[PDB]
Picture 1: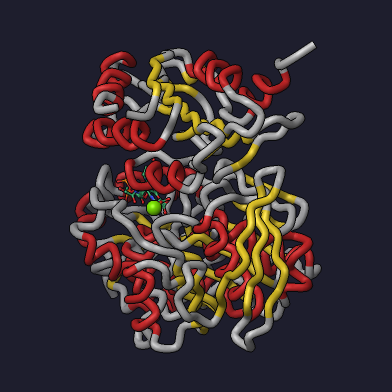
Picture 2: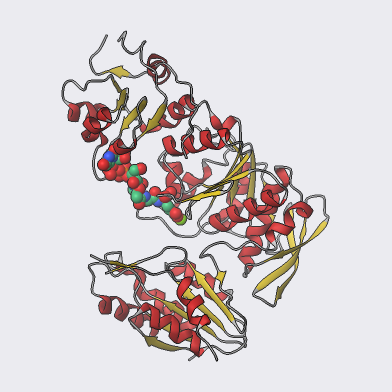
Length: 504
Ligand SMILES: CC(=O)N[C@H]1[C@@H](OP(=O)(O)OP(=O)(O)OC[C@H]2O[C@@H](n3ccc(=O)[nH]c3=O)[C@H](O)[C@@H]2O)O[C@H](CO)[C@@H](O)[C@@H]1O[C@H](C)C(=O)N[C@@H](C)C(=O)N[C@H](CCC(=O)O)C(=O)O
Ligand SMILES: [Mg+2]
């Protein structure tokens, strides 16, 4: 996804815009060169690109200048540390800026012709539910017959094409190029996951958001953000009226202390509640249905109810759908127009129910981490049925997560099966042991250890009873099993297979 019809911008114009210094000083050559693309990865440069040589946690892009020059880069944008790495002559103009990353987004939006002013870009932020919400919006938009584009963790979707992505939210130069390509392909609306990383690090800097939405907040990403406050503030970038990143219109789920705080921040948010608080949109008559679905009445700000049906379980997925409906409405798609696409979309690995022919509920979920697991389980237990859950943790990752995670599983599940999720270099048994240490403390559950992930799934399936619910957690859409080798593995495929192998 790169556009193929970008007119350039003179290098000297860019230099002026961002007030950059030249590494070689007073260039005439700069007045001559044209910039037709922007990238911050040397190996991605196409001839005519500006290479942003950035500093980062693990290296400095200026060390890759030689490579960029050889792939055709017309010029380089870096900081004072960058000039130090380059030492003397690079064969192209080197623009120096303190804080390049804080200005990259605008440069990219300049060269790709400000694609986001020619599109309706919807950004969705929050701790959980970003993916699911972007999926519902994109589903509604399709049903109304709009040409939509989706950008998030599972990948990028435009028209007939679907392609993968390194990050929940791409870096500025990629994002701007994607949006430019979408413009060429005649997309008119784009939904996006906007992570708090992306906001903190300037990834969305040159982008006009027509709608910004907030799902919720609970503790996550504290290995990046120095505190919970900082985490909230990063997200606020999208809602504060005076903020450079304020979206044109704000949709904010209450239901959450953090949610309630964001509404106030936005000052004029369209508010959304599935938990019986007054809001512009509310949910009533929430009923579960056969085939693991949910139906409710969504009441718009005019106070008119709409019959919504959705393939996803859980109260918070009702909240996701309300956010979707609020977004869709402000962008000119009514519930009536939207509902055929919501009735039937499945979001990969987010409470994705797998049905290879009846019996009981079988679901795959992304939920790793203590908090995510607690809510997933709670919204799946009904006094009756029986709830089984297979999971494990990743090797060479903070172990602190393992201990209570099994504890959560112990109080809420009826059957808990501990297996291997990406062990890497770490010894598999040491990982499972620590989770099981949590499963001790059990007056309810029944805990097992089956190392082999495949047999674990097999075990829980054969254990079910018509009406029971099985949950494979901790991978969602993400594949493979790392142990050297990446053994093939897709949680959705085995499980569909395990169900396939069940009877004469
Ligand atoms: C911590 C973080 O935000 N990391 C991202 C960031 O890394 P960095 O600044 O530390 O880069 P580092 O390798 O020093 O590289 C230095 C610079 O030299 C450049 N370089 C480097 C090597 C090379 O061969 N050629 C080259 O040009 C790099 O592009 C980079 O500009 O920029 C790199 C290039 O864009 C990304 O690969 C990297 O994403 C890594 C994979 C990552 O794990 N990011 C996570 C933390 C992240 O972004 N997470 C959120 C998800 C949260 C959620 O989904 O809930 C997201 O929005 O994706
Ligand atoms: Mg997150």
